[PDB]
Image (cartoon, coloured by chain):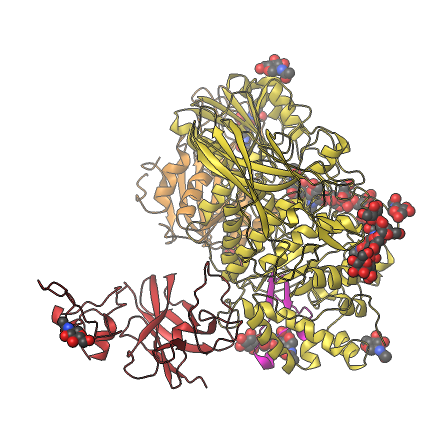
Chain colours: A red, B yellow, C orange
Amino acid sequence: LPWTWGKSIDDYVPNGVVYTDAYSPQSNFTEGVFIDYRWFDKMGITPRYEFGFGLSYTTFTYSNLIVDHGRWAKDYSSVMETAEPFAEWDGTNSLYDVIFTVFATITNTGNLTGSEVAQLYISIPGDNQPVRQLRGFDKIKDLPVGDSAVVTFPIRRKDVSSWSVVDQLWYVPNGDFLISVGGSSRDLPLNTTWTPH
Amino acid sequence: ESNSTQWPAPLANGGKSWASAFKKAKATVTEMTVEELANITSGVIGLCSGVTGAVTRLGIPEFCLQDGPIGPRGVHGSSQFPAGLTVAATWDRTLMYARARGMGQEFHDQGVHLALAPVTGGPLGRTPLNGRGWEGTFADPYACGEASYLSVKGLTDAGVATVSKHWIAYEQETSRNLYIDIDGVSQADIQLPISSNVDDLTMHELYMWSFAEAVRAGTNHIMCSYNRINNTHSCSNAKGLNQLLKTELNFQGGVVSDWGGQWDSVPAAENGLDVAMPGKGFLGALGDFWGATLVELINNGTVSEDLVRDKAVRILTGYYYLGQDTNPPPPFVYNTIGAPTLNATSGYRNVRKPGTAELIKEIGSASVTLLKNTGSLPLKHPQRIAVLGNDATYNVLGPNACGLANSACDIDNLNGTLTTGGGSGSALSPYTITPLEALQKRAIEDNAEIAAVVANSNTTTGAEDAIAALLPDADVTFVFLNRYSEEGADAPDFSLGGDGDNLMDLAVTYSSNVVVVIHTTGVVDIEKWADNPNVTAILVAYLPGQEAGNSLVPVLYGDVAPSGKLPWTWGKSIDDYVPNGVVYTDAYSPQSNFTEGVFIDYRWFDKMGITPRYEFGFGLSYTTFTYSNLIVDHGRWAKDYSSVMETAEPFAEWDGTNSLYDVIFTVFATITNTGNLTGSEVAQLYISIPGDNQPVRQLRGFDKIKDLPVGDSAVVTFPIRRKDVSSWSVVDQLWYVPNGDFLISVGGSSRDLPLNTTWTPH
Amino acid sequence: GSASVTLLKNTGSLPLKHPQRIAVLGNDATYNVLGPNACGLANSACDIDNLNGTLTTGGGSGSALSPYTITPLEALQKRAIEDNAEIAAVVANSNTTTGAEDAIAALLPDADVTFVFLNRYSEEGADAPDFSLGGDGDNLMDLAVTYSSNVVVVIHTTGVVDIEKWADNPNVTAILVAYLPGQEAGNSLVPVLYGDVAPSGK
Ligand SMILES: *[C@@H]1O[C@H](CO)[C@@H](O[C@@H]2O[C@H](CO)[C@@H](O[C@@H]3O[C@H](CO[C@H]4O[C@H](CO)[C@@H](O)[C@H](O[C@H]5O[C@H](CO)[C@@H](O)[C@H](O)[C@@H]5O)[C@@H]4O)[C@@H](O)[C@H](O[C@@H]4O[C@H](CO)[C@@H](O)[C@H](O)[C@@H]4O[C@H]4O[C@H](CO)[C@@H](O)[C@H](O)[C@@H]4O)[C@@H]3O)[C@H](O)[C@H]2NC(C)=O)[C@H](O)[C@H]1NC(C)=O
Ligand SMILES: *[C@@H]1O[C@H](CO)[C@@H](O[C@@H]2O[C@H](CO)[C@@H](O[C@H]3O[C@H](CO)[C@@H](O)[C@H](O[C@H]4O[C@H](CO)[C@@H](O)[C@H](O)[C@@H]4O[C@H]4O[C@H](CO)[C@@H](O)[C@H](O)[C@@H]4O[C@H]4O[C@H](CO)[C@@H](O)[C@H](O)[C@@H]4O)[C@@H]3O)[C@H](O)[C@H]2NC(C)=O)[C@H](O)[C@H]1NC(C)=O
Ligand SMILES: *[C@@H]1O[C@H](CO)[C@@H](O[C@@H]2O[C@H](CO)[C@@H](O[C@@H]3O[C@H](CO)[C@@H](O)[C@H](O)[C@@H]3O)[C@H](O)[C@H]2NC(C)=O)[C@H](O)[C@H]1NC(C)=O
Ligand SMILES: *[C@@H]1O[C@H](CO)[C@@H](O[C@@H]2O[C@H](CO)[C@@H](O)[C@H](O)[C@H]2NC(C)=O)[C@H](O)[C@H]1NC(C)=O
Ligand SMILES: *[C@@H]1O[C@H](CO)[C@@H](O)[C@H](O)[C@H]1NC(C)=O
Ligand SMILES: *[C@@H]1O[C@H](CO)[C@@H](O)[C@H](O)[C@H]1NC(C)=O
Ligand SMILES: *[C@@H]1O[C@H](CO)[C@@H](O)[C@H](O)[C@H]1NC(C)=O
Ligand SMILES: *[C@@H]1O[C@H](CO)[C@@H](O)[C@H](O)[C@H]1NC(C)=O
Ligand SMILES: *[C@@H]1O[C@H](CO)[C@@H](O)[C@H](O)[C@H]1NC(C)=O
């Protein structure tokens, strides 16, 4: 699923569609960033089918979560560049530089061949922050029974940053970032903590 | 102090894309003891062609270095891909890449860390008799360059490090004289390797060109060749490895020796070599100049320890850049060395994926090149079909009977369809789809009869009579010819293999609708029959791999129009090519003077005013194309962003920001399908660079339009880089855009160029 | 062909499932090297030692010309390709061809199944001298049982042949006689071997 499948419309962001005859109709986005699955996770509401859920005819076991801070790369391959300001900028630098890469292993532990969409989520620390934000996916094609495959998630500086309203720039916040990996937004067998400074 | 070399070994720094991998490599190498440094830089015994020693204390595994440039060799459960020669003839960049990507998938899945592939301009094509010219692509620096870029890129994209080969001016097999020292008798006591004697302009403009592109694509490694250059071994040639390769091309990777390519311990260590292969493999018989000897050399002070650290850094950069530490390949399972050199069992693995057979077929259909057609092709629905030649059917001993290198069958054996050549760049085959099978299938769809004479027509009782009785009533007769050649020898002449001469003689005697198909490693002699009124069509299908019949037959019957074109020149005689193409001598120090300069293949033919039978870039379709509206857009330029790695090639126009590979203008032309059938067309662009002793024209563009319908038009486009319009100044030692009038030409071949215009720089 | 091919021995190797490495022995598995009709208007003018391919009919006035032959090798390969398998045939004379014996010895040990195709041509105007197999049939069987323990034998023949040396060898897991199947030799046989249709002839 590319969105959350709730049991009721009443479980989603309130005032999702406003109905008025008023001359100047208003939709206040007071939920903030909390739409779709991050509304359900923050409010402790259980969906019927969660964001990133879908079954196969086999099952996959996740193992061996690795955070490799030496697997970094300059962003050179974008067709055009933004000018988004960020605190860590030193003139030779970018928000879209990959600053580390994370890996994990999946094993086909059921009884048929299958493909698996592995997903990565991150809890970025701060005030009123989502429980989990998706920051990676990798679809393994046609994994035979018993075989394993490594799954790969490049993490950009932007992927681990927050917007500072006061300073008007992106920044990587201080605190503990949880990195979760698994088969859906609520099926996350692997987790680990990254602490920057 | 002890500065023995004129050109010092520059330290690796990671360059552009490998920065983080370099940092890891350097970090690991800093921890290594002298013993460990010598372990990773020298080969050990194993199942693969070559194996680096482990560094077991730091968790660095052995690396499997495995042949070859059509995919993993000596391995079951894989596909037999078409040879480089065959993708070249497609002139299709998409196929060039996809071929290499699929080879890469099968390499990785077999457990290979380093593929001994591709062939990226050594041999390039100085002699059309080169036994392993087939392993390369075009006999042209520009097109070989583009093909090499894409072949490397496809391999590295699959996670397998490339060892692009063979650096450099490795232009004949004869007297290559790999180093052997066994039972007292050293090769050093018999004959040194052939010395390619190459002037500085030729080295830059012809031979280095393709290797520059391989370096830019991110080839992780380079193999130094068997020949000598100016009487110095390529593998310990400091001008070659340290300055040309490592300084000027700014090559950040490892130089690996060819097997027996290293002839000494200390000069190799000082002059650019990074890995000794095979080391302890092959009984130590191919020399073993490092290992414990390199520990001894470092400890007693004759070889710099920091020098050897840089070698180990270069080896590991690829390991870390391609993610082989965190996504390691699975174990390699097959004994590809062979008993009695290595006694060891083989396991089994199947790595053939859906889509790979179909890709190989399509490379075949896109490359098969129509050379002659008087109107016999395409076939309609012929009812009585005759076939001639053992090439139409299976090897009578089985497709893999000739062994791990496709070279151990007896001299007269009927080897069947020549789907690949002989030597280290061959591979096994899960089956062969023979031309006869594919022809018969189609015959049965038309309710027709088909019969093949596939024996040896000279030595098999009744074979001549059988041919005499068969051919007269056939509506068409197909003769399948081949010409096997191999690594370690050059072809003596252009003569067809086996009974090919006699098959043709008989075919034209008894039939008036003879269609010739040639599976071959190179140009052959069909002068006796190509102008025979009974030969109604001729094609060359090169080395099509396992899907030989099913790639061919759809073209013969007109399901797809042929669109392949020759990647080298087809001369009427061997005497028409560059002279002294292969030197035969018993002299202790054999010499090959490259006095022809840049003038090889079509550039020789053009310069000397010799007309080939079929020119470079020639191939017929079942329709015709008309060229129009030549445009040169000096407004359409672009900075070069998209290379994986960067060279340090000096050039006069350098301003601190720009590059040799920026596109400075783009050229366009329009083709119109001007016949009665849909057809694809390879458009080609040639430039006459002004100057003294300059080629008449040099290929600088190609663009293949696919399936252009009758009466429709397409725009064909040709980006031109600064390098594409430059020359090497020997005096100033840099590239520059010369002054004068440049002729830019566009058309369907090197000698069919309806569009021309002039560009004058300032 | 599919209604006539007669299963004489089965130790449990047949029907085949999806074998991944397949070896094939015998010139009978492929074409007449001079063409299906090379032996003339009565299928009897080929040289005594000529490799006549699949014996699809007998010699003499009872013969007939053939528009093609669907060889056993062609049909087996088609099915091997459907199973993503590999397949190799040694189809030369195993006694007189250089390296043929060594190719067989190197191929067979790793094969999941080894098919041996044998024949025995006979003709109008002479009786067979004995039950012995034609061409190199005896030698093919000696080599096959030496190097493989899953040998499936298929016999194309005009009559009874002598298989006493190998009929009770447990390396021979199945024996079938296919008589003279005419033009559709291979495509009648393979569906029986792979169990799309149970053998039914007697
Ligand atoms: C195998 O052997 C061949 C044959 O020996 C090797 O070729 C030689 O490579 C050398 C470099 O490695 C080349 O050296 C340069 O020579 C320049 C002068 O060249 C002329 O002089 C000689 C006179 O005897 C002559 O051979 C040349 O003739 C050839 O070229 C012309 C022009 O195309 C042709 O018409 C002829 O038919 C011949 O083909 C020339 O006429 C020389 O100026 C150059 O300059 C130096 O460069 C070095 C390195 O950077 C530097 O240390 C020096 O300071 C100097 O550069 C300075 O001057 C320039 C401006 O003038 C400036 O830009 C710099 O910054 C700096 O201030 C260099 O010495 C040699 O010509 C070449 N020979 C031939 C015949 O090709 C080949 O490399 C060998 N291969 C291997 C793998 O070992
Ligand atoms: C089916 O597939 C089979 C393989 O699976 C094919 O069989 C192979 O076929 C090739 C040729 O098609 C055949 O090639 C070699 O045959 C003999 C084998 O021992 C060699 O003589 C040949 O090599 C010489 O000749 C070449 C051309 O003349 C030459 O390029 C090569 O370098 C070599 O010449 C040197 O040797 C001579 C000394 O006797 C000198 O006169 C000559 O000048 C050269 O000298 C150099 O090297 C010498 C070292 O020996 C040295 O003394 C001297 O100083 C100098 O440095 C040729 O390659 C294979 O052998 C054959 N394989 C087998 C197993 O038989 C088969 O053809 C195919 N079928 C069909 C129908 O095509
Ligand atoms: C120098 O290189 C040699 C050859 O690579 C090293 O020896 C080899 O060390 C490897 C470990 O890296 C051994 O392989 C291992 O075998 C075990 C089972 O015993 C298996 O569980 C592992 O997965 C791995 O495959 C190998 O046996 C051994 N080979 C030989 C011939 O001794 C040597 O250690 C290296 N020296 C240094 C100082 O690093
Ligand atoms: C292939 O067929 C030919 C005939 O077309 C066979 O040759 C004949 O064999 C008989 C014995 O059965 C001889 O008495 C004849 O004289 C042979 N005829 C000729 C013209 O030589 C041949 O034996 C067959 N090949 C094989 C391998 O069995
Ligand atoms: C939206 O926000 C403003 C204050 O920013 C508030 O006064 C207003 O009543 C809100 N409108 C609705 C429809 O909730
Ligand atoms: C150093 O050791 C090597 C090989 O053991 C030897 O060839 C060389 O001569 C030695 N150097 C000295 C100074 O002994
Ligand atoms: C062409 O074929 C006919 C028989 O079809 C033959 O008589 C004639 O001599 C042949 N011509 C040449 C030049 O081969
Ligand atoms: C190669 O060139 C030199 C001159 O540079 C010449 O003297 C030598 O004899 C040439 N070699 C041959 C084999 O002609
Ligand atoms: C059966 O085959 C095996 C090899 O697979 C061989 O060792 C054995 O001798 C053979 N036995 C007979 C009785 O032929």
Q: Is residue B16 above or below residue B26?
A: above
B736 is within the stretch colored magenta: no
Q: Residue furthest left?
A: A21
Relative side of B586 to B347, left or right? right
Q: Is residue A126 above or below residue B474?
A: below
Any part of residue B562 in sight: no
The image quarter containing residue B618 is top right
- Is B604 in front, or is B651? B651
- Residue A137 at what x, y percent from top left? 36, 67
Q: Is residue C64 above or below residue B617?
A: above
Any part of residue B587 in sight: yes
- Residue C151 at what x, y percent from top left? 46, 50
The magenta region covers B39-66
Relative side of B419 to A168, left or right? right
- Is B566 in front, or is B115? B566
Q: Residue at x 19, y 67 (%)?
A: A5
